[PDB]
Structure formats: structure tokens, C-alpha cells
Length: 195
Length: 195
Length: 50
Image (tube, rainbow over all chains, first blue to last red; front, side):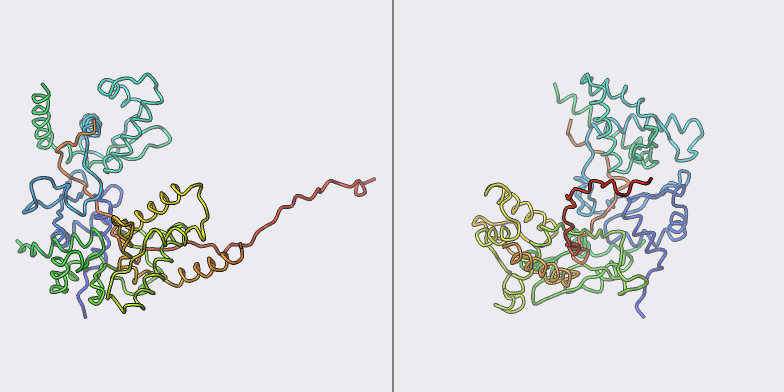
């Protein structure tokens, strides 16, 4: 009697909300299920003041806060979104990761999601900005804490046995040149004020 | 394309999901909005396998898994709900609060008044089963820690200026009260056995 | 270091809907106590084969 949304649609949308994103390369059937009824999932998210994005060439579907009438102050204030705001250390690691990601994407275009890197490559980068506490293990722990936070934001896979990680494609839409330029203007303002 | 859902209803739904709860004694606005518009909210929750029950006598509304009882498996697992199993201390505390709340409802009827208890009565009853952690300061520290965690789970409020908490009416709708009664039986056996 | 940047929220996820029914509670039913086998089991040479 009562209308029920297609079971597969409900499953896919609930899981996508759970994880905030979804890759064809890892969960193809749910990706294709969503792509079969994108209007349906957009409709489902509409009451939540949440929204959807698509990147076919990278095979990524990611949620994004609806901004039709929400306060421009910050989408982070939205009650449902749980993980807290990003901070400029995480943003620095994000910048380095984005650089590595674009370098990888040059090699084989968008290619697969296998944007691999060795942890030993990141530490030299951070040492320049965050400095050198003079204890290799200490800086390794610091980097791993930052990487854990980013994985909490879904931008990086957890480490593995080879001390390698793979950059989640979601980065391409957080380090979107538009967002990068907005951040860059904000940070230029910050430095100007710093005087 | 689609007409935007009523702003007030979207706010009520998102706030409700932030706490799985609504209360006329605290938030009459969203309480009334949902009360007068149950079909809209229920339809909004349909896609995610979510539904709401009510107790107007208690002035309460709450969320629940819309999945039909034992649809394919006896006990349910849901992507957007994590079933935490309280540690024995929390289980004891919630059991004592549940029995106190039901006793209060016997005293004053159903939903006539929100139950209450002071730290004065609390600490002896907890130390009855838990003993001395090492000091009175530690006693109160642990007590307030569990109280805060329960408040995070929505069961209780933080103590007021007079160190009196209010037992949230939500307590009436716990999942497995039989398990609580069994653990209470074990506790009331151990209290006599160990003394 | 801990300043908040203005980057937009993308890849946002929602979890931990606080459903009261999700609660479960502790098990203590395995209360049987296995006392110590502190007794001295030192060998007695009677078994020793010829």
C-alpha cells in the first residue's frame, strides 16, 4: 500500500550518506545504481539541505552541502555534517597531496584511483614549513596524526604495510582551483593583517 | 525544478536528526511543526529507512528504524545508526535511571513531570555496586563523566546549579529492557552475595 | 596552527544518527569462577619405564 523507494536506491543513498562519497573503481554497483536515478537521489537529499556532485571521468560521487538558502557564513555550521572544519595544517598537507595528485594525473590522465606515494616523501616537505623538531620519529608521528585527520575527512587512505597511501579522488573537488583561489585570497589578507 | 520543501520543516527534521529527539518542554517550535506535519517528515525519512514515534503525553518525539520488524534477519544493522553496547558501568547507571524514571511515572502518572535525581542520592547508589575508585573527588569525576556521556546519548541533562539532573523522557523507549532487567537481577544478586 | 580555513565542505558525510533503539547493554553471564590450580603436580618416578 504505502509507497516505498526502490530498495537498491535506499541502500545506495544510505551508504553514500554514511561515507560522504563513493567511487566506481571500488564499489561499482552502487555507483551505477546512483547513476541510474541521479534525479531520485538528488530528490532524496533535498529535504536535508544536502546535495550531490558528479565526476564521471574520475568515477566519484560526493555529497555537498546545499547552499540555496543556507547561511553563507559557513556550510560547516550545518547540523548533520559531523566532522569538524579543516585547519591550515591539514590544508598544507592537502596542498602537498594535491600537488602529488596532479603530478600523478599527468602520468596517465585521470586513470585509476591508484595515486600512490611513499610516506618518506611527505616528511621532507612538511619539515620545511612545520620545521624540524630534531627527532625523525616525532615528525613521523606528527605526519601520521595529520594523515589520520585527513582520512577522517576522507581525503586519504590509511597507511599500509609498505608505508604507502593513495590519495582519494575527492581531493580534486576540495582543492578545486576556485576553492584554492578563495583560500589564497583569504590567506593573503591574513598575511597583510599579520603586519 | 522541484519546489523547495518548507524551510521550517527542513530545519525541524535536521535538528531532530541531530538528537534523534524533540521535546515540547524545550523546543516547542520544531515540536509543533513536526506534530502538525507528520506525513511530510515521515515521507522525507522514508528513503533512509527512518521513522518517528511520539508520546504527546510525555511531550516527546523520537527517531526509529523504519525497517519492518524482522524483515530478513532477527536483529537489524543500519548504515546510519551504530549500535553501541554500553560498558557495565554505563549499563548499571542507565538501569538505575530507568527504574527511577518508571517509579517517578508511577508516582505522578505518565509524562506529568520530568524525573529528577540529585548527586546526593546518586553517589551512594553507584558506590553500592562500584565501590570506592580511590577518592571522593574521583567518585564525582566518574559520576559526572558518565552523566555527560549519557547526555551525549540523550538520556540525561547535565546537573544544574544544585547538582540535580533531569531524566529525559526518552528513557521510556529503550531497545532491550529485558536485558536491563537481567543485568539488574545479576547486580541485585551480587550486592547481597559480596556482603 | 589551529586556525580554521575557509575551504568548502566537500565529500561531506553524515553518521551517528542518535537512535535510542540502537543501544545495547553488557553481558556478565559468564560468571563462573575458575579457581587456581596452584597444587604442586611434581612427578613421581613410578611411571618411569624399564
